[PDB]
Image (cartoon, rainbow over all chains, first blue to last red; front, side, top):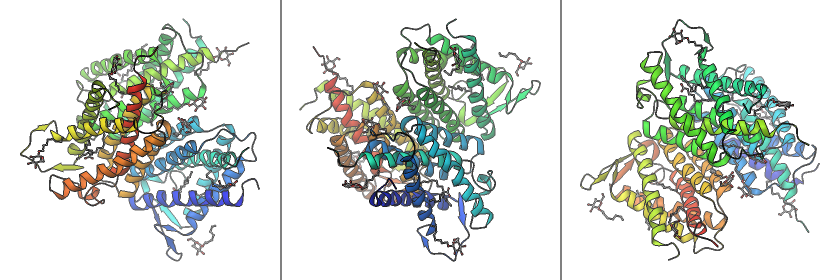
Length: 189
Length: 189
Length: 189
Ligand SMILES: CCCCCCCCO[C@@H]1O[C@H](CO)[C@@H](O)[C@H](O)[C@H]1O
Ligand SMILES: CCCCCCCCO[C@@H]1O[C@H](CO)[C@@H](O)[C@H](O)[C@H]1O
Ligand SMILES: CCCCCCCCO[C@@H]1O[C@H](CO)[C@@H](O)[C@H](O)[C@H]1O
Ligand SMILES: CCCCCCCCO[C@@H]1O[C@H](CO)[C@@H](O)[C@H](O)[C@H]1O
Ligand SMILES: CCCCCCCCO[C@@H]1O[C@H](CO)[C@@H](O)[C@H](O)[C@H]1O
Ligand SMILES: CCCCCCCCO[C@@H]1O[C@H](CO)[C@@H](O)[C@H](O)[C@H]1O
Ligand SMILES: CCCCCCCCO[C@@H]1O[C@H](CO)[C@@H](O)[C@H](O)[C@H]1O
Ligand SMILES: CCCCCCCCO[C@@H]1O[C@H](CO)[C@@H](O)[C@H](O)[C@H]1O
Ligand SMILES: CCCCCCCCO[C@@H]1O[C@H](CO)[C@@H](O)[C@H](O)[C@H]1O
Ligand SMILES: CCCCCCCCCCCCC(=O)O
Ligand SMILES: CCCCCCCCCCCCC(=O)O
Ligand SMILES: CCCCCCCCCCCCC(=O)O
């Protein structure tokens, strides 16, 4: 693989911490509710949740490095700004989840579009699309299995929130950027 | 005129679609209520609403092309980012309309100022001012005619929301940018 | 001092006006409540409030000019954009203060991180840290003295809101930028 193990671990941990903050926000606001008492929880989340998101973060970063022309000009502040945009968008969905589906979903889509315009490229959008499909699909399956549920006013996408599509998209764009950064920041001559 | 017909039509449709999303958001949250049952509606809006906003979008873009030095360096992502900023701001007003007038209006003004700082120029601000006056004036007349009304906690500007001023301003800045883009993206040598 | 008196006065007034808008927003939404009837108020604030924040604005700008390499390339739109970001963040805290502490605090921290990534430098972050400590410390003392109080759902940081830390941080970053601008905009050859 193109990421070094240490880089993959840092990205995994980054994704895990951001996931725990966002998922705690969803749980405490009632955006989601878990129904899986048999597993160990970490904060408000089943232990496998930050592992799934952390693994997705490292995986999408790796994916970008297999797509054409990773950008060598990516900076730490672009990456910090991107992580902040995704986390801010994530927690915002917790704050506004009880509002009507159209303005809520449009707001998240606007945040995701702006994130991509500022920070992303073509391959980054591709990674964004991959997880914007896979992310919600995994959630839909987990919800049908009774593992957790969304609030009834935020479950319009086959049991899950429509805002997941642009939320995951923005996540993929930023994870891709993190992969580019991991390579770019290596020692140079 | 400086826009080609095809460009004017694309801008018209862009404005119309964004208007329908924002206006649906206002209606469904109770920010506004229509009182005009005799006309055909499109989604939540009287059919003439997206036509008015769509026409304003093409008109403000055209206006910019008659003002000094349209920028040749405008990009599709600046335009996408600007449309996203205006739509995100529009739907946000639907979410926060019931809150006190000062923080609500200040929030929209901040979003509009940031939009202009990132994307706008002097002539763009001029176009912004034109519609920040005309937009609210048209709405005030329509409200006095009983065509629609604002929620009583969002009607402080002669029957309409004070946030319309910075919302329309941001709209004008972005419409101007769309006009610059329409010309810039034409085939080059 | 490095600021000229006229520059320091403009920064003082800028900070004072922004403070009055943000503090009115906190009072009218019930984020905070004053308990000091014996002093003259200006709008919703004790007269000393805009003086404290105004003085802090000029002071942090001055501080930046004593730190390494003030940037000569700072622009008026960066400064306007930064002031808008801080004011927008400030009024947003008034709108969301009743929500759970983690998503509220994370949202403000994201806004502050993005503000710094876009506009700040190392010394700007240093100024940010200084006031992110001093600001909340002053408030904690004032609250223990019974001068004002936070809403019970926004008082987790020794009687004050945890969001003050990233809010003041963003304030310091932007005040520092204003100091750089004051020098940069002086007449050139
Ligand atoms: C992109 C998000 C941050 C990832 C950075 C942490 C990954 C660690 O990566 C390692 O860092 C070392 C010290 O700089 C370097 O010597 C190695 O070349 C590099 O692989
Ligand atoms: C990397 C993704 C997780 C790796 C370890 C898999 C742990 C799965 O654990 C499973 O979780 C379910 C929901 O909580 C429970 O219903 C199952 O009984 C439990 O076995
Ligand atoms: C919506 C997402 C916003 C992300 C904001 C980060 C944008 C970074 O912006 C740029 O980043 C580079 C790294 O410092 C620097 O060269 C520039 O000074 C900075 O303006
Ligand atoms: C600014 C918002 C997008 C407007 C773009 C659509 C307008 C269509 O405009 C036309 O597009 C053709 C195909 O590229 C070109 O050959 C023509 O020169 C151009 O006028
Ligand atoms: C381009 C702007 C609209 C062009 C067609 C004008 C249609 C106006 O239609 C009018 O709308 C009013 C409010 O709904 C009604 O009160 C009037 O009875 C109706 O005739
Ligand atoms: C508040 C409004 C935010 C609009 C964000 C769009 C800013 C665009 O930002 C810049 O746009 C250009 C077009 O891709 C590119 O050259 C740059 O890579 C990109 O950072
Ligand atoms: C950084 C926020 C804005 C501060 C600008 C106002 C400070 C006034 O500053 C003065 O302005 C004069 C007129 O331009 C100049 O001739 C002086 O050199 C300058 O010191
Ligand atoms: C620059 C900072 C303020 C300068 C003037 C100091 C005015 C302080 O005034 C004090 O304010 C307190 C709270 O309102 C009251 O409890 C005190 O009785 C009052 O004297
Ligand atoms: C979160 C804080 C966002 C602040 C947005 C302001 C960023 C300014 O952005 C840049 O500012 C310079 C001054 O005009 C110009 O050279 C550029 O055209 C403009 O894009
Ligand atoms: C860039 C770092 C982001 C890490 C967090 C990514 C979150 C992706 C969205 C997860 C949504 C999970 C859910 O709503 O149940
Ligand atoms: C850049 C594209 C934006 C199209 C939408 C522009 C909206 C302008 C504001 C319309 C407000 C109408 C109302 O609140 O009744
Ligand atoms: C850049 C100009 C910003 C001026 C306003 C700065 C506000 C700093 C935060 C003050 C918070 C006061 C309070 O919540 O009581």
